[PDB]
């Protein structure tokens, strides 16, 4: 029923909490000092035994992770209603900001390189049987070539959807593979959507689009239009900006309508190697 | 496309708007919840409705929002709710507008059982006339006409609301809400080019819901229309795109009305009736020259 900070392999004496780094839908995330760290505070029901042990399920898993392309998970302490996830602090900016910054050039060699980093991290997490469930450019950090994946697994315990009208954030729907898109309802619950390794590969496809177009797909369209277009399998390409066939074929594969036709992260890494 | 009794009220509203000067938070006292709250201006004795849209973005974009929003002072019509001003306060932009004491027809339909055909004829003239004004005098389409944004009063006007005046304010919105009642046209769902025809589809669908007392997709079986007289978002929307459109029951409504909605609910927007056609449709020619005390029906059903 409890997770204390002495259960972890990071020797911890004191934890300072500094300013809030930013707003977000799942808890609050502050600067901290341990070196410097990022502290995400979460609120739970005093006795929601269901969700408390569900949460613990996930966090012991994270204790086994260590990989250069995944943010270093450092510890989690429980005391209801207050929970904390402590990770390493990312220097630099999110990939979201970098792509949308006009002063940074993002050539095709570099986009292939960034994409390859994200895939290595994702294949590691998959190899350890951990699904991300919220892969996206606001959850990737880039500092002069170092690329780190963050916030994996959180979505299960997230509650970012929370009468009879489902809340949809800009950017969310275009990362959701069709099998998921076809099941959203105002009764939908984060812990029961049919996420899979295949849905994670789909989400990487949206990032590849975003890397080259420097904007999300379906940028123009309202949510309902996006749901129908994506649910029936209509998808953009990159020919309108002169991207070659090879850079577009990865999208055809990652966004494939039937999941089993989408590649694992291992095969996808190979496909990215073979670009010019 | 001009009347006098209507002529008296428009300047009078303009005269009222003279009162406002400028707006900010402490001028206003929360009266109730309707998100939009009915509030009382103290610098000027007006009772307005003020809607609070939560946006959190740096001022250069917010200044663009308000300049684009300032055009509503200029559109003025007996078929459009009256506008007073838009300012930003404390991470929310406020739009305060004429208050309509009857609410939305969404909200009116909840209290009534179903809305009778002759009143629905009248509301059809109001809505059709509003979009035509907007299209012809401001080159704008509404982009979301449906019952919650059409407002009615005890004085008896029916006017449109919440239309797309500022391309950027829609841009600035972080997140949208999708429930199980959609009024989006088939062509908008498919992401193809669209016009005020999309508003005409939305109007047809709203009319059938109000006439039957139920959102009509999926269509009810024989059991529930008899008594009248668990669905995922994607498959509701796909119903709109691929199944044949809803229709009024053939027994209880005049042919003119049925044909009126059927012309609104044609899937191909090029074949759907456009704005002027409906002004010449048999159904609204009949309804135009009719005597219904709309104010009377309203107050009796809602209790005022
Ligand atoms: N490990 C980290 N290092 C540095 N900044 C971080 C870290 N994790 C999160 N942040 C920042 O903290 C803020 C809140 O992040 P978060 O709560 O994950 O929401 P988000 O990913 O930005 N978008 P969303 O999940 O859709 O609400 C953002 O400004 C993040 O960039
Ligand atoms: N001027 C008004 N006078 C009276 N009631 C109003 C007015 N404007 C809005 N309402 C009511 O306020 C409630 C919420 O309306 P609103 O905040 O505009 O969102 P909504 O209509 O419910 N959904 P949406 O139309 O998509 O923005 C509804 O019950 C409306 O009927
Ligand atoms: O409120 C608005 C709105 C949007 C844009 C804009 F520029 C406005 F000025 C707006 N309001 C407004 C306008 C004129 C008057 I006269 C009074 C008003 F309150 N809405 C658009 C809406 O339908 C949402 C929710 C449903 C999906 C589509 N966006 C509801
Ligand atoms: Mg995040
Ligand atoms: Mg509204």
Image (cartoon, grey):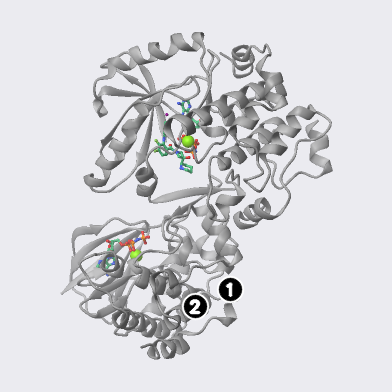
Q: Nearer the viewer, residue A103 or B154?
A: A103
Chain hosting mark 2: A
Residue B174, position as x, y percentages in the image:
38, 51
Left or right for A74, reference A247: left
Residue at x-position 37% and y-position 85%: A120
At 62% across and 11% down in the image, what residue appears? B296
Mark 2 lies on a secondary structure that is helix
Q: Which residue is mark 2?
A: A254
- Vertically, is B73 above or below A11? above
Residue B204 spot, x, y in % from top left? 65, 36
Q: Nearer the viewer, residue A57 or B226?
A: B226
Q: CA distance from mark 1 to mark 2?
A: 9 Å
A106 to A42, vertically: above or below: below
Is residue B24 visible in the rendered structure shown here? yes
Q: Is mark 1 within 8 Å of ligand 1?
A: no
The residue lying at 30 percent from left, 40 percent from top is B65
Residue A64 location, quadrant = bottom left
Label annotation for residue B86: none
Secondary element at tag 1? loop
The reply to whether the C-beta atoms of the residues labelled 1 and 2 are less than 8 Å apart is no
Tell me which corner region of the image, top left, top right, bottom left or bottom right, holds residue B283. top right
Q: Are marks 1 and 2 on the same chain?
A: yes
Report crowding for label 1: few under 14, some 14 to 19, many 20 or more residues within 10 A (C-alpha): many
Where residue A201 appears, as percent x and y from the top left, is 47, 77
Between B162 and B38, the residue placed more toward the observer is B162
Q: Chain of mark 1?
A: A
Q: Residues within 10 Å of mark 2 (few under 14, many from 20)?
A: many
Query: Where is mark 1, residue-wise?
Result: A257
Could you say which quadrant of the image residue A57 lies in?
bottom left
């Amino acid at each position: 029923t409890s997770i204390f900070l002495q259960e972890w392999d990071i020797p911890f004496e004191q934890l300072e909490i500094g300013e809030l780094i930013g707003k977000g839908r799942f808890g609050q995330v502050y600067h901290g000092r341990w070196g410097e760290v990022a502290i995400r505070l979460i609120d739970i029901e005093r006795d929601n035994e269901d969700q408390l042990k569900a949460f613990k399920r996930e966090v012991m898993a994270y204790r086994q992770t260590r990989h250069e392309n995944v943010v270093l998970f450092m510890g989690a302490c429980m005391s209801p209603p207050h929970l904390a996830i402590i990770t390493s602090l990312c220097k630099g900016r999110t990939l979201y900001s970098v792509v949308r910054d006009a002063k940074i050039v993002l050539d095709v060699n570099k986009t292939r390189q960034i994409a390859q980093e994200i895939v290595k991290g994702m294949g590691y997490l998959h190899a350890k049987g951990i699904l991300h469930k919220d892969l996206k450019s606001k959850n990737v950090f880039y500092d002069n070539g170092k690329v780190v994946i963050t916030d994996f697994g959180l979505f299960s315990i997230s509650g970012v959807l929370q009468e009879d009208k489902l809340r949809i954030q800009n950017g969310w729907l275009c990362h959701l593979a069709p099998e998921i898109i076809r099941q959203l309802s105002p009764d939908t619950e984060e812990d029961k959507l049919p996420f899979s390794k295949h849905s994670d590969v789909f989400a990487l496809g949206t990032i590849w689009y975003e890397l080259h177009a420097r904007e999300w797909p379906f940028k123009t369209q309202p949510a309902e239009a996006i749901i129908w277009q994506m649910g029936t399998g209509m998808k953009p390409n990159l020919s309108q900006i002169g991207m070659g066939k090879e850079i577009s074929d990865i999208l055809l594969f990652c966004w494939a309508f039937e999941q089993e036709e989408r590649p694992t992260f291992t095969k996808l890494m190979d496909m990215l190697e073979k670009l010019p | 496309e001009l009347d006098e009794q209507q002529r008296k009220r428009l300047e009078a509203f303009l005269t009222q708007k003279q009162k406002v000067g400028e707006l900010k938070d402490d001028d206003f006292e929360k009266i109730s919840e309707l998100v939009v709250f009915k509030v009382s201006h103290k610098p000027s004795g007006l009772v307005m409705a003020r809607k609070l849209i939560h946006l959190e973005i740096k001022p250069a974009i917010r200044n663009q929002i308000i300049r684009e929003l300032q055009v509503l002072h200029e559109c003025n019509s007996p078929y459009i709710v009256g506008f007073y001003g838009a300012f930003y306060s404390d991470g929310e932009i406020s739009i305060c507008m004429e208050h309509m004491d009857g609410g939305s027809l969404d909200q009116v339909l909840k209290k009534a059982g179903r809305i009778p055909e002759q009143i629905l004829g009248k509301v059809s003239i109001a809505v059709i006339k509003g979009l035509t004004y907007l299209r012809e005098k401001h080159k704008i389409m509404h982009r979301d006409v449906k019952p919650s944004n059409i407002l009615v009063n005890s004085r008896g006007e029916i006017k449109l609301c919440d239309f797309g005046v500022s391309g950027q304010l829609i841009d600035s919105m972080a997140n949208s809400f999708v429930g199980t009642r959609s009024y989006m046209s088939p062509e908008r769902l498919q992401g193809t080019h669209y016009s005020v025809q999309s508003d005409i589809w939305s109007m047809g669908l709203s009319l059938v819901e109000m006439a039957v007392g139920r959102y009509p997709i999926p269509p009810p079986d024989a059991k529930e229309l008899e008594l009248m007289f668990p669905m995922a978002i994607f498959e509701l929307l796909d119903y709109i795109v691929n199944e044949p459109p809803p229709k009024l029951p053939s027994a209880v409504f005049s042919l003119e009305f049925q044909d009126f909605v059927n012309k609104c609910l044609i899937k191909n927007p090029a074949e759907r009736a456009d704005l002027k056609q409906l002004m010449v449709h048999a159904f609204i020619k009949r309804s135009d020259a009719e005597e219904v005390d709309f104010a009377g029906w309203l107050c009796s059903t809602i209790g005022l």
